[PDB]
Image (tube, rainbow, N blue to C red; front, side, top):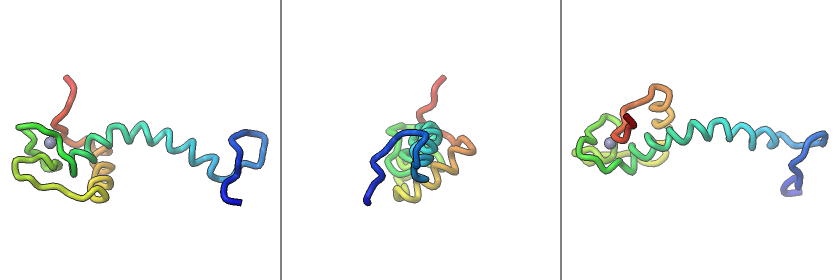
Length: 87
Ligand SMILES: [Zn+2]
């Protein structure tokens, strides 16, 4: 049919059984990634926003959401600079 109406164990679950599980792990990463993803295309709203990776820069220059999502991944792994930290 269209979708296997199930969400159990000891049964013939599809390969999508692992998908719903794996996304939870990387969703934790996504929470920090959103800071960079939004910073790249949306911005921050800061005076000292002048960062290599920012939309809210005093230059007013940004990227598209696809360009920002892939780069936010690349910023997550290096832990890039962020106008909204926590002391
Ligand atoms: Zn910024």
